[PDB]
Amino acid sequence: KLPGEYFRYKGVPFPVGLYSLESISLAENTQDVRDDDIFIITYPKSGTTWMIEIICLILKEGDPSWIRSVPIWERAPWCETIVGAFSLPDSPRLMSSHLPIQIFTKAFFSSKAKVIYMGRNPRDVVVSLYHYSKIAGQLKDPGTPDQFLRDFLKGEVQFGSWFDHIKGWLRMKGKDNFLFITYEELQQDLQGSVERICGFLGRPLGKEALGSVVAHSTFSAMKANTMSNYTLLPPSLLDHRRGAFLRKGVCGDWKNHFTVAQSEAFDRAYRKQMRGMPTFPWDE
Ligand SMILES: Nc1ncnc2c1ncn2[C@@H]1O[C@H](COP(=O)(O)O)[C@@H](OP(=O)(O)O)[C@H]1O
Ligand code: NA
């Protein structure tokens, strides 16, 4: 029953069918936030999945049992989707959200709940989102790469502007219950990143569990795990016949997608938007 259209909530674009004024509004206003609750927030296609699998492996201290038997989307449910983690009985609760800070669960700000925000090179996010839209049922066709790029720069896509998203959420940097990390940092030193996240969550791991979290967190291990690779999804929601959720899993694929002209227009957009921002791994 997916149209591949957008509706708006507080001025932000949401895919029809998987979201509704109610589901979003409920996520925004719920008072149900707990001190040991864990949230993973990202702009779509930045590697949410990667992070979800890593923390599921950490919570079970390295035992692959849980990630092998339960679908990735049921282990870290979305807060705003029609079937939200808030609209369910299931602690320690692990949840996911793509909502931009000005819409995310307000009760969070005065709580002790933890949040890991993950950022990825917007260019690579563009490519991942481009391909994914073709096989994702809730998303309309990208159109030409060039038109898709313009849409992305205008924030005419699910969850709005990538620039607004990351800039808003970085406003939390400094609070001890907020960790900011990037796809590039995980690609560069997965183990190093896993230890760092263990510290953040107050969940130390022996050399054994650690090696195990790293092993089952690898792209190849994950693409190979049925419960984790989205292949149990209805073809009407994700066309398996035509593509995979876990597409390439690398850094830099944007250079094979952007024409030089597109790459130069993007840098102009980026330069204006990120004027006072700090330097990110992907800033070359
Ligand atoms: N373990 C892993 N290692 C590297 N990339 C991973 C990964 N798990 C997921 N990804 C990548 O994260 C993107 C999906 O993001 P999200 O989960 O936020 O929607 C995909 O990028 P690509 O399309 O570039 O391959 C996917 O391959
Ligand atoms: Na689609």
Image (cartoon, rainbow, N blue to C red):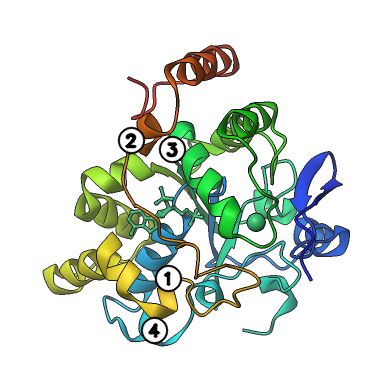
Residue, disc 3: 124
Element class at badge 1 = loop
Ranked by sequence position, the earlier of labels 3 and 1 is 3
Q: Circles 3 and 1: CB distance less than 8 Å?
A: no
Asked if disc 3 is less than 8 Å from ligand 1, the answer is yes
Asked if disc 2 is less than 8 Å from ligand 1, the answer is no
Element class at badge 4 = helix
**x 34%, y 52%: residue:** 249
Element class at badge 2 = loop
User: In the image, which disc is placed on residue 229?
Assistant: 1
Q: CA distance from mark 2 to mark 4?
A: 32 Å
Amino acid type at mark 2: Gly
Amino acid type at mark 3: Asp
Ranked by sequence position, the earlier of labels 2 and 4 is 4
Residue, disc 4: 66
User: In the image, which disc is placed on residue 252?
Assistant: 2
**x 45%, y 63%: residue:** 244
Image coordinates for residue 226, horizontal then vertical, percent: 39, 79
Element class at badge 3 = helix
Front position in the image: 113 or 71: 71
Ranked by sequence position, the earlier of labels 4 and 1 is 4
Ranked by sequence position, the earlier of labels 3 and 2 is 3
Task: Please determine whether, in this image, residue 266 is positioned above or below residue 134.
Answer: above
Task: Please determine whether, in this image, residue 159 is positioned above or below residue 132.
Answer: above
Amino acid type at mark 1: Asn
Amino acid type at mark 4: Trp
**x 86%, y 63%: residue:** 22
Q: How many marks?
A: 4
Image coordinates for residue 211, horizontal then vertical, percent: 16, 67
